[PDB]
Image (cartoon, rainbow over all chains, first blue to last red; front, side, top):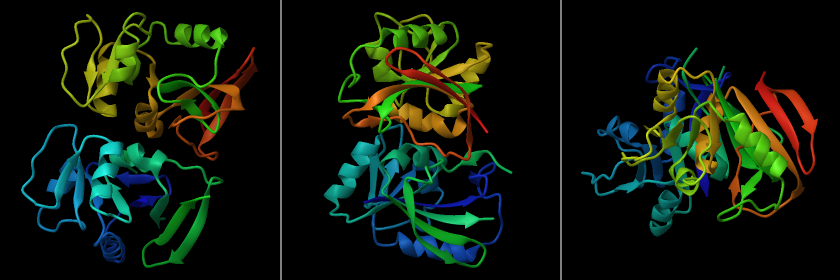
Length: 154
Length: 157
């Protein structure tokens, strides 16, 4: 299954300028990074290179509008949602996570099975709006700085 | 203002592996083609390609990965929502429409200002869908019955 990890405020903002409107949240950062640590990740090309020191999962399916060969042996290039899913399927992935950024989210949201949202309580980039009546809140653990929600399709 | 125009059955289906899944409705097509007639139209490369004999507004902002040469005097290229708004800002346009396909409606949904949606009335089988939208975020500006569909104009809250 296809699932996205995202931390977003009440107005659905995920980013202002470049990154976070909000400050600290290491509770959040421990959480998501543990979550995706052993399964394939799907990410924008700039987020990939913004994490060259500490790469996000089992592998990385990198969304590029351009053909790219990578340094890392675990990095892959996908040009579409379909191609990404095929790469993860060739990896024998059980699940693959969509961690950012905004264009990638919008793009994958129609194909998403589950959503691990960190509800944070003014910006330009956004997490896509979902139908509240067509997703069941599977879990809602209260945490430090935010409140983690896993949302499944009905 | 960015505004989409789409026709979907119940299930939000907008197609089946090539074309419309529902048959007739030329009152849809007349009103949709005339709607977008003069303003710029945001659309995909394959949707543009297929529409080459007709072509929907006065200038077409073609959303594609590849940087492409287009020998059509006004049919621009875009690699993002942002670039696509810049180019319509450049053409002095008031309104920019998203004609789609499915991936493009998705990419433009968090930026939309309006949705102009024709609700074709039965359930159909498909594979390409128009995106879901939160009930709390959108207000229904108007809704009219016509033959074979009902056009809805949804403004954001």
